[PDB]
Image (tube, rainbow over all chains, first blue to last red):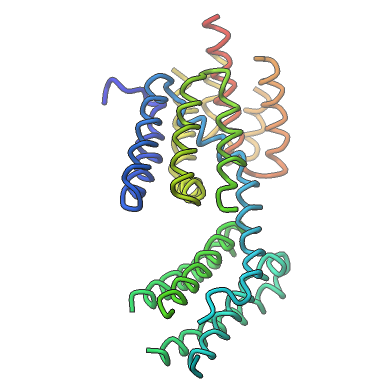
Length: 185
Length: 138
């Protein structure tokens, strides 16, 4: 506590929380990475800080990457395709939602087009919701959670102007849709 | 591929710290390589989680900048996170390898008025401080 430098704080304030969240997904990876960061930090105080700053400086790469995933999500046209009417409706709704979500980076640079896109996305989410209700619950609550999270992300975007948040939330909503399609399969 | 941000982000980040430390960078590289190899897309999640803790990081960087006051150069540089809010005061405070880092800091300041991202100013200030330390110790 009193022996560890102040510069080593980002380890425990940023890296430790991440490693703890990872400890549920994979204990070995979390433990290994944590050990590496501890070694590196003790041998070189203020290293984790420099790493995080270096990451913040290469943020454009991450924006380009997330946007790339969002655009390439269009190639997931008929992936995870499920033999019954409601199943058809389901497939079409999921497809339409993912397809309209993949076109976000095109419309986000124009307020009008982006707003209309928000309209269409809202309609798609509502229709997919109703269709899910037809097919009928954890995946549902997940989808809703990430949906309202996407809305709140939009709310945050209209203040900030950072498109990367929207891209990430959209990608997560798409991933959720895919997960639900897997659950149905 | 989802394992791209490993090489695209972490690889150059580790590579651009090999002058201060060597083996630590290699151990970090190895750890990330294995963890991503067994669990694809993990590095992306980590990077995103780090980007999510942006506020805490900016706060700490500000604190780290104010901490450098404890000579005139350091004290003037330590007031930045509290003077940059007011444009006039910030202007006056602006008026108030190492040399390369100084002019790179100048470039950072010049880019700030285009961006508005004071975080880069904080970082470059801290690196200027680290360079002053690097010079004074040698």
